[PDB]
Amino acid sequence: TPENIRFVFAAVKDTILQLNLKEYNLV
Amino acid sequence: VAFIGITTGLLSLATVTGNLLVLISFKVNTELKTVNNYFLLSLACADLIIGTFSMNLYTTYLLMGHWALGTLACDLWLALDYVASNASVMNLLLISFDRYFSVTRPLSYRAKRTPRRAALMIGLAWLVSFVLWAPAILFWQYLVGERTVLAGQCYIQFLSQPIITFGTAMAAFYLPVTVMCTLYWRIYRETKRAGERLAKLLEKFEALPLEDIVAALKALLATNRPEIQLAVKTIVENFPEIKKEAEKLTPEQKAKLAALEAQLADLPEELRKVLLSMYLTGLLYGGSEENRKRAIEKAARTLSAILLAFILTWTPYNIMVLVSTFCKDCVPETLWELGYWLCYVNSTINPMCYALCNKAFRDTFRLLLLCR
Image (cartoon, rainbow over all chains, first blue to last red; front, side, top):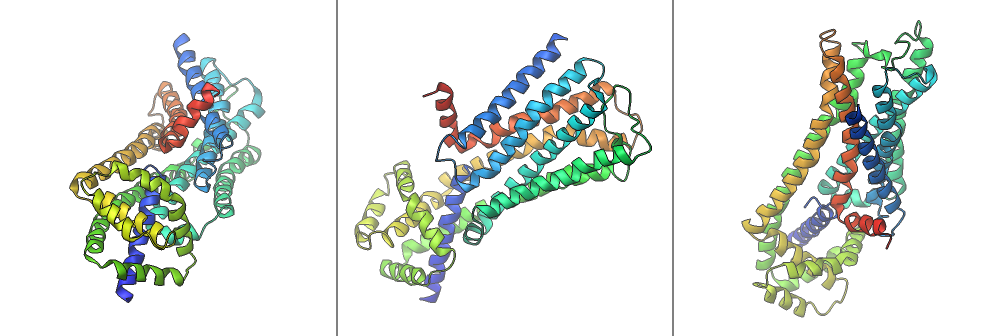
């Protein structure tokens, strides 16, 4: 559903953000 | 006399070897070639230039009473030193900008900049530094009434310019010394909020149905966007690394992850990889206060170290030259040389405090040093 897909996109964006923080060792 | 020469040679050797090791490592292994490391390489090159052509040569002039290498050598060395210093500052600022834009626009930024664009930005910063500093000094030497500094001195004549000296100093450090602070403060805020909204999202995920999760993920993936494909590629290629962090995760809830994988056995890569790499990161970094507090404290400590080091090492000159055209002869000439040396000192610590932290160099440099 629209809202569900929006939440999924938010979650994947957050996962990418955590990955990016990890890659800088700035976690 | 011995102490001065012994505290400068060791510093020069340390800076030179530290930056040369990074420069070689960037072309000594295929693992650090990532585009994110180009800024580190430029910063290391600028620091190496400083440590190999300024620290030793400044110590030479400070030990004796005059830079008797002639009006050419003095001006050229001075221009090279200032250009290298501003190159270092610009590279630090650019690294800060990339750090800020890599946590606030993850998909957009990661998908809106590939290779050449980064090299373009690095070259732009270098050219900005060169155009700001190198031309003005020598063009003034040629266009001023006369090159009137001293028969053996090497200090720049631009120091007596309320509209220029203060202006240059501000545009060189007063702007980046605050942009870096603001950007890193925003990064700290957005990594606290990131943890909070990740914990909330993970709780909602736990409450949400699984079949709907799969359907929504598949529908989002089908409408491939410019960046969603890149994020999928990154997550899938990194997944083996993420799983290793699973062991670090407590076994108290390993049943949940195992079960989620069990139902996710189908859809091998497109759904299973992303779904697991999302659930695992959510569980591990949202968690509760126990882990979130430790993570935020570690991030804040690293940020504070990186910032404070530069901010406290690069102020022994900025403020002393701001007063210089404010209080006439207010400083002791003996002190000036201390801030002069402190700037170089910054240029030395910088590779250590920026490159080793990545921890892929931490072992690679040691292995290269052992030659095996």
